[PDB]
Image: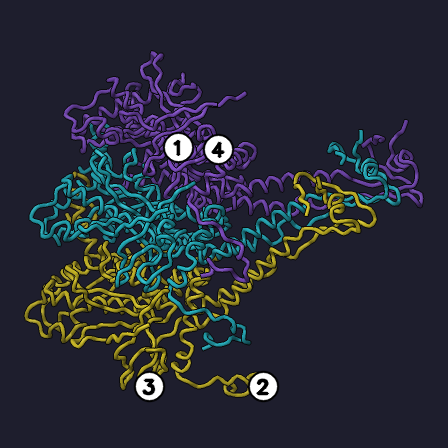
Chain colours: A purple, B cyan, C yellow
Amino acid sequence: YHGGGSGFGGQLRSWNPPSESVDAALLPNFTRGNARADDLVRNNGYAANAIQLHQDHIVGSFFRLSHRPSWRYLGIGEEEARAFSREVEAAWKEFAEDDCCCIDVERKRTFTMMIREGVAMHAFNGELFVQATWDTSSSRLFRTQFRMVSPKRISNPNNTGDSRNCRAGVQINDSGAALGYYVSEDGYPQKWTWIPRELPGGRASFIHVFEPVEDGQTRGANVFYSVMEQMKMLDTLQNTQLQSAIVKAMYAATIESELDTQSAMDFILGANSQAAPVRLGGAKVPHLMPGDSLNLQTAQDTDNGYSVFEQSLLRYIAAGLGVSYEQLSRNYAQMSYSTARASANESWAYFMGRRKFVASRQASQMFLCWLEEAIVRRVVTLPSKARFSFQEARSAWGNCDWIGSGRMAIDGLKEVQEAVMLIEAGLSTYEKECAKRGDDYQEIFAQQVRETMERRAAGLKPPAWAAA
Amino acid sequence: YHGGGSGFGGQLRSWNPPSESVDAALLPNFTRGNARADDLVRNNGYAANAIQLHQDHIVGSFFRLSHRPSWRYLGIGEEEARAFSREVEAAWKEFAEDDCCCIDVERKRTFTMMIREGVAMHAFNGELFVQATWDTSSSRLFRTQFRMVSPKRISNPNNTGDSRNCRAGVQINDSGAALGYYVSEDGYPQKWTWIPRELPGGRASFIHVFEPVEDGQTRGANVFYSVMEQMKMLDTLQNTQLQSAIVKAMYAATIESELDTQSAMDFILGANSQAAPVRLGGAKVPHLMPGDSLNLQTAQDTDNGYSVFEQSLLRYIAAGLGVSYEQLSRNYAQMSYSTARASANESWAYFMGRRKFVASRQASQMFLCWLEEAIVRRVVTLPSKARFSFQEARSAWGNCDWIGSGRMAIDGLKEVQEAVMLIEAGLSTYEKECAKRGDDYQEIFAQQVRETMERRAAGLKPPAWAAA
Amino acid sequence: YHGGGSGFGGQLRSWNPPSESVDAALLPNFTRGNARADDLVRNNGYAANAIQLHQDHIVGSFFRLSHRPSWRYLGIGEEEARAFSREVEAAWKEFAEDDCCCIDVERKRTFTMMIREGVAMHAFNGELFVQATWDTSSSRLFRTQFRMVSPKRISNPNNTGDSRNCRAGVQINDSGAALGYYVSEDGYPQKWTWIPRELPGGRASFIHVFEPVEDGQTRGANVFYSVMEQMKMLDTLQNTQLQSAIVKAMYAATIESELDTQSAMDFILGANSQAAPVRLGGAKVPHLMPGDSLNLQTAQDTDNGYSVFEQSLLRYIAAGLGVSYEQLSRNYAQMSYSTARASANESWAYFMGRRKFVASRQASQMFLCWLEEAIVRRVVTLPSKARFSFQEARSAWGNCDWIGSGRMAIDGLKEVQEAVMLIEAGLSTYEKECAKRGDDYQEIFAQQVRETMERRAAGLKPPAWAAA
């Protein structure tokens, strides 16, 4: 095997990367990497475009709840489960979507915008932090509130060095689990607070969502590490090329003469001395003595293959980040239907995975945290004859699924024909087909049974879905 | 035969590779090869893209259980087998998919995330290790927990040399079988523990999944050995080319004169001395004496054939890794439907093989480990009059199949038409067609029989699948 | 005839190859050729791709048994043959597909994985060896075990010279048949054992599978001898071209002056002395005295015709190995449907031949070895009133056919239409149509007759295959 060897001619003799865990590689330069990722996101067109694509495709314009408790395990009954789910869904829908935005302490974000911010933070910071608090002064129906904590705030107190149990502001028990986090207080023009992960009663107090790569990993790594250097180098190349083009296009001509500069421009260029401005009106034919000369400068091609090199670098960056090349670069060159569909599918697989993990876990944990007080305050009533209480089986009572914006297809008619053909056979159900369009099938049925009554009352022809 | 000969003109005279086992080639430089593969994965856009493609296509966004015990062998009866399968599937679904993430000791990953991490570890490290433990302090329903052990941790104690029976921290019996493993403890700012492969009762304590190449192979080899050198050399070429382009684009022009440098720029470039900055506003025509000169530099083509060489190297890398060229390089050049379908099939065969072996074996062993407690703690009851106990035939009781995300078609209508035509004939069943879409046909049937009742109750037109 | 003559102008005067058997050409340099093939497989991207294609297409993701005993010969009856086949197939499932992997001594591979490893070994080593042993300490139902022996281990004892009867560790009787083998024991940081080919009772103890080319051939030859030299030379050319491109791209410019190097770089390049680093920010216009000079280097085309030469060499290599050019090189250039189908058929013929011979013979012999104990231990009962007992006609009792993964075609709809039309006419049966899809028609019928009952019980519309 030449992987561990010296190389072809010994070229890989100096390539001896150390063997170390993910923590040993990531933690020493965590803050610098995060700052560089933030710099790239704020001040580069492509990084901001990638973040916007992540936000728009992973979550969308809405994030909707679907409460499906496991009634078999609980032994309560299907109808009671349906009634409980309807009540819980109504309560959650009013709680999250108030215009006062009292879901968060800062009163600036709704639930959907909070999910989008969490996804964005997971993108260029590798993780997201959420804290759940209670305000006693509040007289509203619910006291639960959520605060989005930036990863920069969590760090070791007093800027102390890492230990075996405490790393990067995270306290670790004997196992890999985390017991608590140290959150700093930021003064824009310091102190640290201990926040336990979970309350003694089992409620989740502070939320941390990230995907671990190796066995022992305390905090996550942003996606920009793969292509961080190339983005900066490409920005430098773009600025240099633009400045060079401006400079080369500036010098249009050159005057050579042995006379005074005022005299030379007077006799050759045509300026009026009554250095010296020249009027652009008209065409001029100067007369030159033997010593005089007039040279019109020629410049190189403004874009001499910079476009193709930029194309290659943008393909590399899009491969590193995960978004499609066309989406990142806005190129959308000529291509057949099959190629566009294949690229869309390749991007959609990654987007679906990100939605399934990050946003779904965050929303599920927030929903469980809210549901615990909702049940405690008797806003909703648990079904009777339950095998287990809410505390004993939290996941069983609070099992849920989340629906986001569906993919907008290149051909609208083909997808509709496919859906109709699937519905005609037994391969698919109404729920799955409506969920692909970002709709709830029960709401569609209610709207249809309302519309048929409205049509009948007005005297119009009954709709297709109506039963004779 | 010229294979063992000197060559055409004697060119292969120095090519005399040693004849040795896979262990003799792999073990001496195991750690350096693993470290180089990790370096490529962390810091190259293409390697990270390949790992992400592996994770997404091999597993997907979900990994689902299908329990099919062999009822004929055990002599229990079909209906008891179906009831047992329903119970164990429900228990597994609740156990793996809790939001508390209590399946693993570190409480960071769900079952699907652990499967994806195992696939990733198999990709760039050549193997995956899983440890199953019990916590007695836990008061939950199940005490089983799983921990993913990095391959770096398994090594010979005290960094001692390999022996005949103990190689790379694995103790080997007279045959090729492994009896136990030595796992180190990592301190981020050492000691070794003996972990037997199997408990005395026959339970699996330590899990090791990899594909052997030759007869005697203690540990597996990463996939990057084939293309390790080329990726590093291509990265060096890319960085060098980018720096060279930036350098050549930087120098726009050149001034030649015998005067002072400030005066030369004042009279020619146009800088103001009130070295010296020059304003970009306007167009200028300087006046030059005989000794003076102005030269506008021209540069070579920025991308002069680098794209084609990069294409060739990327095809080589994609051949080595196994992913498609379009997926790896994000190129997706103009191509017909047939070529895209052929490349997709060529990649899908490899992905299906990897899913059938690695993830399936890992998930099956974890499921058996959980099922042993589940049966022991009497959460589920074995059918009566069974020929053999659970211990005597573990595979018969725990026979199962796993379903992941299905391939996304380039043309949605064509696959639906194909599935419908197959269903109409006897060549296919409902289960196989639903499995290709990542769905369970029994859940679809339950949803349909619920939806028909819902439509009937609300007064809507009965669905197609309903029976008159 | 000029084939044996001097040539056109005497150019073939030195071309006088010796006339010798295959053994005389192969045996003297067997080990060096095998080592070179192993080196190419481990360390070249294309060779690994070819081996992976062999494994994926010849075997696939599964290998399945179809027991077809010849009842007419033995005069037992069709129904008894069916019952015996069902029992044997069930028993072979459990032995081969246990998760404990107790089929092999090393407990690392399942039956399909051992078949794939055998195919791979036949690919780059020219043959495969399998050993069947018994473990008395085992308390399981079956004591049969299989060990894949690397071809390197079999060699002459004490590294002695070959004889008339003993060549390369294989003892040959008066005829060409082999009586036994000498297998060495490998110590990774020596002794030889005599293993007879067959037990005295007729059972197969040692398995050797290879295709003979000529009359007397003791051991087989790998496929790589045809194209090993070209692969090594192409790898050298690729590495040299990459290094040359990096070297030529590295030198961006050149400074010529009579001053000191520090002064020259300060005045021309723009470095700061407060050798000398230069910041890349901005565009610069240096001033040069008559002695000074600035030159921007221009390099040759990075990929100047290397791609087409690589294409030709890859076509030659793919022709030598037997795989299609597109599969080997991942090129998949623009091409019509007919050309793609023709290339796919050309490759599929070779893959079907390899599957029919190598894997089928290996699996059949292993199945016979297992079936002998299975019958002896009375796990399965032979039908009564049989003409010849198991010993008299092993092949008649153990006649079987093996099924692998079916070909993935470019157009899914066309293949389904073709299969439906063939089924409608009398040209084809259900078994052949289901076999091309890698399915067992009896299993499909059982699944259909279950699904129709499941649909009827739930109240859904009866399936198409149901009989009124």
Q: CA distance from mark 3 to mark 1?
A: 74 Å
Disc nearest the viewer among 3 and 1: 1
* Secondary structure at numbered mark 1: strand
Task: Respond whether the residues carrying marks 4 and 2 are from the same subunit.
Answer: no
Q: Is circle 3 on the same chain as circle 4?
A: no
Q: Please name the amino acid that badge 4 sits on.
A: Gln
Could you tell me which secondary element the residue under label 4 belongs to?
Answer: helix
Mark 1–mark 2 Cα distance, whole angstroms, equals 83 Å
Q: Please, what is the three-letter code of the amino acid marked with disc 3?
A: Arg
Q: Which residue is mark 1?
A: A170
Above or below, comparing residue C364 to residue A101 in the picture: below
Quadrant where the C terminus of chain A lies?
top left
Name the front one of labels 1 and 2.
1
Q: Which of the two marks, 4 or 1, is nearer to us in this view?
A: 1
Q: Position of residue A466 (x, y in %)?
A: 26, 28
Q: Chain of mark 4?
A: A
For label 3, the residue is C164
Query: Residue under circle 4?
Result: A52
